Amino acid sequence: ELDQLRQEAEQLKNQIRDARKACADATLSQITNNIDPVGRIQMRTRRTLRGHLAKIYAMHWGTDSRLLVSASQDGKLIIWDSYTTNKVHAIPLRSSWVMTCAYAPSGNYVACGGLDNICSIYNLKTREGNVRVSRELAGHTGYLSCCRFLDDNQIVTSSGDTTCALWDIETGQQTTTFTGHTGDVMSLSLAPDTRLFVSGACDASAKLWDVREGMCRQTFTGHESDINAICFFPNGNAFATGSDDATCRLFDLRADQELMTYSHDNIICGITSVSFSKSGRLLLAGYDDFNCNVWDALKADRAGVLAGHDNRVSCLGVTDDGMAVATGSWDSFLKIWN
Amino acid sequence: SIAQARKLVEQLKMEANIDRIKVSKAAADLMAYCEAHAKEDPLLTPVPASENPFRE
Amino acid sequence: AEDKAAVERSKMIDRNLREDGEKAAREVKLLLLGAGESGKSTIVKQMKIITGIVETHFTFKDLHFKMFDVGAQRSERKKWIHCFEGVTAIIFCVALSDYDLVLAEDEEMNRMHESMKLFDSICNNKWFTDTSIILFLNKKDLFEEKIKKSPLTICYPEYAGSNTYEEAAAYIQCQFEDLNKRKDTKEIYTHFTCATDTKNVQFVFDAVTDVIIKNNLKDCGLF
Amino acid sequence: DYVNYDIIVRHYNYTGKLNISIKLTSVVFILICCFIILENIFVLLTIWKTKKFHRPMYYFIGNLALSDLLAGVAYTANLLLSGATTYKLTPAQWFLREGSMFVALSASVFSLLAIAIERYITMLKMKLHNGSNNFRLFLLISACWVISLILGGLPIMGWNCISALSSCSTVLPLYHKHYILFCTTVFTLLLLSIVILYCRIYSLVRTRSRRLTFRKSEKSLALLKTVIIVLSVFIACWAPLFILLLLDVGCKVKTCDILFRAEYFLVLAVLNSGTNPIIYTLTNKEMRRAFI
Ligand SMILES: CCCCCCCCCCCCC/C=C/[C@@H](O)[C@@H](N)COP(=O)(O)O
Ligand SMILES: *[C@@H]1O[C@H](CO)[C@@H](O)[C@H](O)[C@H]1NC(C)=O
């Protein structure tokens, strides 16, 4: 009976709820009550990258902590050199409607995508030639929301068709498909080990996926709207989610339960980006109110503001060495902060 | 319908039987990790101006 | 030694970027929207004589147009609609012959009402407050023939008027234009399309010219 | 010479204005000038406090506002330092006092011309987006202020009635009648320029609109109303003083009595300087919202 097999699901929901509350021994705010606070984090604009003539929708750092790539709606993918500020490359995308950007760990390839439902991979180290398109991955039914390399041959992508996919750049075929989300997947984040990854969707939940097996290990709820951004904690045992309900939440994998909520009454707009600092003690979150707030991950108190943009901060990233923060916005500028 | 309900209940039963940990232990672990790496975070500890590539 | 070459290459890239930008700033941008079985394909086919998102370029009377059709996006629209903030106009297509047809719901959902709901959502959207809408009412001959057999009361039960083509057509136009709450910032240009018109490109051209004049007067402060 | 207290007395005696502290009408005019000053301060405060207003067109509007502010300040000073203070002044101080007024009013008129030129260029091009062509924005404002300074400070560096006493103006006894003729000609050219420019703007809009075919004017009538308001409020408020100066160049000393009551025409011109912000901020429909 369909009626009987629907009733059962509520029983397992109740069982999970109870098995989780049984683990609620003390809130993170208590175990972390006596640690000294961080103090005000004052950061200033070191650089200002100019050259985009439209909104900037994504950015990603390279593993070298010096080169970053940015994607704008003017149909340009620009590879900068943040130190000297000079444009190393400018790639004329075929589809101007890009909303994703990635930089391979090896520094050889860059990926992008968007409303074209395709993930384009451009090769940067081609013998005595200009940057040419290396590959085009086309198996998604919705727009491409996020993509991240695993190595020079594998890439994970999230789409608005409520599905994620692990690809094979050599053959261009979907190696694995991750299903289970009920809404559009808006962001994804790889773990340091590259064995698991979490995804946040518009169904107001996040899911942890196993890359090699393809199953959903755990599901996390609590947000009251779409989850726009998701980032991993440096040690790989927790993550953070920013939503349209003007709130961030910290989840722990081996607890299966929300730990902390970063919110404030004066903040009512949505969150567009979240990232951690190299130590994981700071949580930088970009907002639609044109600002980027620096939360203290272990406590709740806010500890900084990065106000430098005339339009909303759409993308936010931190270098692998933790030396600088990059912030893009709809005003067509990028800023580096120290 | 029926297959979708079966898939949902199977996923929920797979998510139920998981070895969980008390939130106190997880909080202690996060605190320990952040405390061990506090000296390697330029954003946390502004580095000397001579060693910062973006000021030089 | 290698820094000078780097700055040279960066200056060259900036030059190319400026050229490309000032060339792209001379193109009209149109966002094509409509219900399922509207005359989208007909409109794009008759305007081209001059798996994602389809882009159609064309030139008419020394003016270049880029029209973007995004009907193949079954995802939630509120997550990517803002990508089109700044287009020159929105071309919205509505099928008149849908006034007597039901949707896949097949219980109480009238297809014309679904199209009307979509138009109401798009017109009053927070991103499109100053952007004008070119409305194309398609299937006008099929409507003309159908409105002789089944009265228009099947849609808009609060309707009382002649059962002839001109009256009902004007009535539906007014209904679609009464949904415009932002009646002070944007306009709604309407035009009854057929399978064979030969003059829809002209209408889009004139509407865009009017929008350009209005934007210029707003730039000077003269309006 | 330029340090003789007797030159001013001799000229005022010759033109029939010799009279031997703040009178009935001075206070009301002073408060009107203060009102003008604060009005134009508001326009600059709002133009500079809003990121959307950082295009070249609000720079021209702000330039006009600055000119109107300077005109108000100059008129306050000229009204305080006139009257019984005229005989406590040196001819150099007298020349500075009058040149301040000439420079401020000329600057305001040239700012109106600059706004008209920018509007005419924007409509004629009729491009999809208007870029900030900064070269024109700095090459017009500089021309306005430079021409104003050269024209207003010309009598002090010669070209005055000191040597030849017959060529005196009744309204400004130490000025040359030919200088007043020169300034009136410049004003006439600027007025014709502004009228022609706005008429061509209206003609362009109407002609381009009439070629469009729609199913269901109103936008081209509002343009006519705004153009009519602008040109009427300019000509009406500047025509009395222009006619006064022409009459003042026309007749010989002591013949024309009306010339002695010239402080009404001047206050009307400064009233135009004060009315400009109302017209260039009421008909915008976007500065109204930014005000609050
Ligand atoms: C574009 C060119 C525009 C040209 C501008 C024309 C300027 C016209 C200003 C003419 C009047 C200047 C100020 C003179 C005022 C006198 O009436 C009193 N100061 C005399 O007062 P007394 O000392 O006798 O009491
Ligand atoms: C003014 O000039 C007239 C005619 O030259 C002269 O008779 C009269 O005495 C003069 N008055 C003064 C104060 O100089």
Image (cartoon, coloured by chain):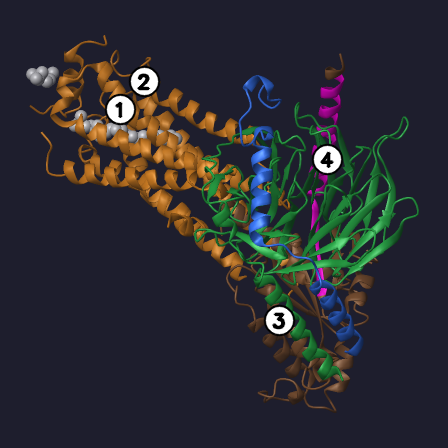
Looking at the image, can residue A336 be seen? yes
Q: Which mark is residue A14?
A: 3
Task: Point out the stretch of residues depicted in magenta.
Answer: C5-33
Q: Position of residue A188 (x, y in %)?
A: 70, 50
Q: Colour of chain C?
A: brown
Q: Nearer the viewer, mark 3 or mark 4?
A: 3
Residue D23, located in which quarter of the rendered image? Answer: top left
Ligand 2 lies in quarter: top left
In the picture, measured across the screen, residue A93 lies left or right of residue A313, that is right
Q: Residues within 10 Å of mark 3 (few under 14, many from 20)?
A: few
Question: Given the image, on which type of amino acid does mark 1 rest?
Answer: Glu
Q: Is residue D165 visible?
A: no
State yes or no: discs 1 and 2 in contact (Cβ < 8 Å). yes
In the image, what residue type sits under mark 4? Ile
Residue at the spot of label 2 = D155
Going by the numbered disc 2, the residue's amino acid type is: Pro
Task: Give the CA separation, mark 4 to mark 2.
Answer: 60 Å
Chain drawn orange, letter?
Answer: D
Residue on which the image places disc 4: A78
Which chain is depicted blue?
Answer: B
Same chain shared by disc 3 and disc 2: no
> Are the residues tagged 3 and 2 within 8 Å (C-beta)?
no
- Spot occupied by residue A45 in the image (x, y as percentages of width and height): 54, 30
Kindly indicate which chain is depicted in green in the rendered structure: A
Tags 1 and 2 on a common chain: yes
Residue C16 drawn in magenta: yes
Whether residues under marks 4 and 1 lie with C-beta atoms below 8 angstroms apart, the answer is no
Between circles 4 and 1, the one closer to the viewer is 4
